[PDB]
Amino acid sequence: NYTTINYYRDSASNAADRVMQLTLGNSTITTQEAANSVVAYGRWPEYIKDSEANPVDQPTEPAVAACRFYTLDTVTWRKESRGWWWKLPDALKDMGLFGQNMFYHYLGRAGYTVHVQCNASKFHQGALGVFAVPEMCLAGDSTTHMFTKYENANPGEKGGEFKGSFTLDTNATNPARNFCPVDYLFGSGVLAGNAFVYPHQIINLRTNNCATLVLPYVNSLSIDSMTKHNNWGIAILPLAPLDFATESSTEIPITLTIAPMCCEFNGLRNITVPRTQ
Amino acid sequence: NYTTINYYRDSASNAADRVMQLTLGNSTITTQEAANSVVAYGRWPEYIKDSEANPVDQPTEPAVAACRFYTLDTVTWRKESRGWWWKLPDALKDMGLFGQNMFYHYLGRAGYTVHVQCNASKFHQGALGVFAVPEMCLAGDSTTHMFTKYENANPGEKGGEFKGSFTLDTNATNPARNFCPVDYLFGSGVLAGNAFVYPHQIINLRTNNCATLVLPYVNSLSIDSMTKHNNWGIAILPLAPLDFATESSTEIPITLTIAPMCCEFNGLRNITVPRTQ
Amino acid sequence: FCGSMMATGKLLVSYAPPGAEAPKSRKEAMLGTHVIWDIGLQSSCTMVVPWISNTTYRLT
Image 1 (cartoon, chains in turn cyan, blue, green):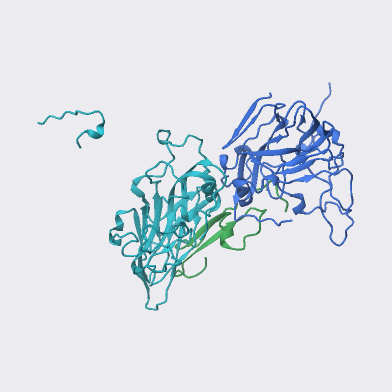
Image 2 (spheres, chains in turn orange, blue, cyan):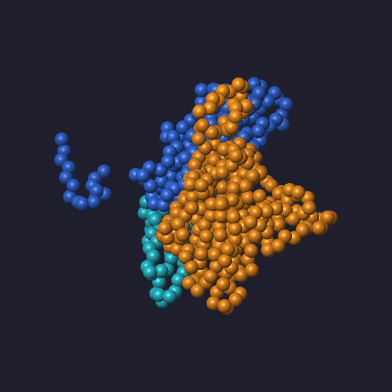
């Protein structure tokens, strides 16, 4: 036994599976070759509780008007693809009434259902790692730290691509001020092979055609500014390169469908019009 | 006594006050010089009941996102003003997420809270009749019947003005195809003095500064196309002309604030982009 | 679907209630009622067009 007694007031001073259907609003997704679906950290998206509400004004919950699947621009997977990234809610800023509520309010909160679709025949090869990264900070391309500008950090539904090797932006007069995400460094100075600590799913073309990730709202705050802060980052990397019948030049589309969930907005004002690239 | 017996199957064959606050969504209206508020036909707006639902697909109810006050362009009341008209939901087609839901869906339904505001001093004169007319059909300006085109019939938030006298559009090559609403005929071949059969309020500048009309959804159908059909028409007429201290040239603003209520939309598709004037 | 067993695909069958422009591309069509049909062991798909009408009856 030992005896412990606190001699101070403040406690700081104390000693230390395959067939699935997803319906949101007026949108429905059917899948037959699914590898199940992952709920990030086992937490389903939810609305702010009265015990955690910071803003006092009544929130607006568009529900089905905004809690529905929006499909982003399709990308092409080739043998030379290094990977793609999107930022949420940034990727949905021009998507129906969700983007309208996003830009008309000072504070916004939403979870997501991300559905990545990549169908290929039984004679194709390749694997895609689909990772949901909270606070997916990406490295810049200049000797100046944290120098990436807002326009490039928020590409929108197109997102960005990973790079095979790091290139330094030496243009002093007109710096690019863009990201330089290196695929094997995961764009953030960490080995990509460890990226599986994040919620993820692998689309192995021999097994499944799609991946589904249910992202809860993750943040150090109950609600934040959606225009300032991207809660999530979706990163897709080719773990196994695409291959097909030795024909070469094969390319298959990857489509991304994101549904915001449990959307809450506070602080209605005039609409925000961010500066464009 | 008399005896009646039906000899057929189908039954058709058988013989024959001042201080008020209105909060909708994130919008609030305070009034101190109100002449109460009228509920048209004594019916409060409501959602479609399961016993009357024609469409089968799940509706979307944006609630606070669209059920909120939008303020239209202010008009000017002069001594020479003959009156103004707006069409609902046409006047709100470019108003936030309400217009977005209106154009993204094939079917829409909504009641309204119309708040007309016209403040003047205690040394002003004039009365405004504010009338809510179901199916406010207006007369055209050509010898061709029913020849008014869609672009003019749906002016938007600006609405239209009544005319002192009827003018015929004789331009055969480029007909105006616009309305010609005559103020004393109420724009529809009926004496304006009888327009009080419609739900209405009078803004008498010596008594009240505002009028409030709660319009239920009125139609021969439970739900209709908002782009094709204007459920309501708001007509404002000077019953007593504006006058002030004999100074002349006096003009006071009239502002219109409409909040849709109990919005229901069905038939989600790609957005409708109507042809512009 | 009356192709071979070795054929695979996904179709989108869409119903748009009236009022807007008739959908000229899949991007417009997916905004209305629709079903995504996967052609596999089951070669038939049913899309129900729901009764969405202003009037209680339609003309023929």
